[PDB]
Figure 1: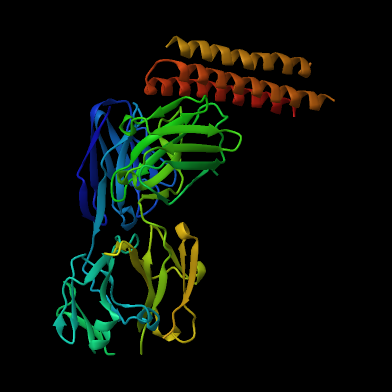
Figure 2: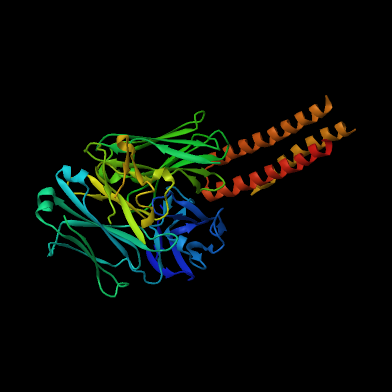
Length: 210
Length: 215
Length: 91
């Protein structure tokens, strides 16, 4: 049963670059098909019968090859070409897909806009207090996010979560969630989020009291 | 307009059977050439073809799911059913149906997919807390806490507010329940005048919540 | 291989049965010629369908089922076109 190997499995490139993805098969297939899948969407057929373009697919895409070796080419990468690309063969049962290739965009540096949110009164009525920090629209993904609480640097008690790269501007957004007991929350006064990032010449701190 | 739409439970206990149903329109399994197939995608992993059925009722199954699959059709209803026996945690995935043709031997139209979690745990609806701005640009949001299983959807002002929205992927907390936040940037000026309401939908528990976010 | 030739001929035959019947029409009536149109398209569709079944039943590769089904679709379509042209000769 026919297995496909895609290279690379990951790839970063600037807007306007030519990008190439190769899919070598374990044995001869008469045709290779290509799917594009964006963040939490169903795969969309992109290229079929090796080189033919599906509908609503710009000309900057193309495929070629035969036998065991095939390529997908994007001739000038756009921000909305951010996706995972899979090759697929229907020449033999079982049908199979390649492992995929993540295309990421490289762009210029953008500092995060930083915001901090205190826990709601509604939540504090339960036992928990969730203090949230938002880093909004930045590049690159790399970022340090530190929690100070009456100036004690916290540890092991916040989770970070990050969005997929934006399809129009290629930035990231990130939230950091410091979770506490109401007991521990009311004990202390001033809560602070401290962001470090390549586009900030010196770190940025947002804070609050109560 | 070819459309497909997968339906079935969000949650299944280990060892039990999962019954998925594709409903389609704009084409028909009574037409010569037509086929429907099922594909699944585990969270963050590769697509894996599972099964298909043809208009002449011929069937194929992936040997990797050895003997746990039954596919069947109801032409008149435009419905294909897929049954997966003895579900285990590795079967947790998004399940898709898609349309295939004897002219193609590839899938040209897919449903949106339906998410299945295999777990012994019970359905639980979220609690939603506002993330209030204080005092150019302000931000605000909703914290959506303590739900099981995935997914929830969040929208703002019932779809009329989309620009500047980020809804973060969920994290499984040490309690076994998921949490996420959705946030949006708006101009300071609109605070206190424009209403901001966040619409949280958690279909696996049939919960809907609408939270006003005020300063 | 020979399946190309058999189908290309069989489908050509369909448009001749039309070519004949339209020509004696050419030699209640507008109704009659629209009936003949629907019949001959229904004959092309049915035959297409029949061939696809036979193709899908054959113990061959998918690529081959695909070449054969596309060969057969293209002729069937070329026939619907040629016959659609004959209705226009009446209408």
